[PDB]
Image: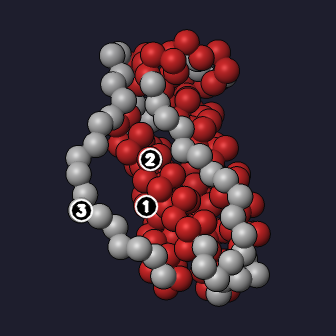
Amino acid sequence: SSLPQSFLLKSLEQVRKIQGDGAALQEKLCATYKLCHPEELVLLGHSLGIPWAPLSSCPSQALQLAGCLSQLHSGLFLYQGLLQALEGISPELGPTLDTLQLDVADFATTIWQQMEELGMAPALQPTQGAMPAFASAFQRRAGGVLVASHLQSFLEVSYRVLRHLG
């Protein structure tokens, strides 16, 4: 209710596309490798050490709409980095990961353009970051399960946030 329809309608459709891409990934990981349960990969997740992206309530404000979207953008950035570090997982899964990355990037672009319009502090000079390490094919594959399930949760919440700011 606070953002232009061009942004609202596009941004929701972009989320749904990424959710569908992500579901495809999840389904292929389960069917190919029998990795079907993120909750069975707790000890692996502990070893990987990944800081999953937070979201948190924001008012439909003049002076913090941009800050609400900035959290979404910062989470998308974290997820894009995780998707990148997977390096396609396997030749079977590569094209599905490529599609998911492209769709994530398209969404992030839309978010960033809206943050500019709303009035955001400029980004600081960038720096290289660190990545998760997958010590094996199995860790890449199980890491893919974890990344995807947390990305799904971040998307479900993002969709709600966008409807709430709409």
Please indicate whether residue 44 sits to the left or right of residue 125 in the image. Answer: right
First reached walking from the N terminus: tag 1 or tag 3: 1
Q: Position of residue 40 (x, y in %)?
A: 64, 15
Residue 33 in view in this figure: no
Name the element at disc 1. Answer: helix
First reached walking from the N terminus: tag 1 or tag 2: 2
Q: What's under tag 2, amino acid-wise?
A: Leu
Query: Distance of mark 1 from mark 3, alpha carbons?
Result: 20 Å
Label 1, on which residue?
105
Name the element at disc 3. Answer: loop
Report the residue at 67% width, 44% height from top. Answer: 153
Q: What's under tag 1, amino acid-wise?
A: Ala
Label 3, on which residue?
125
Report the residue at 51% width, 70% height from top. Answer: 111
Q: Quadrant of the C terminus?
A: bottom right
Q: Mark 2 and mark 3 in contact (Cβ < 8 Å)?
A: no
Q: Position of residue 6 (x, y in %)?
A: 61, 85
First reached walking from the N terminus: tag 3 or tag 2: 2
Label 2, on which residue?
78
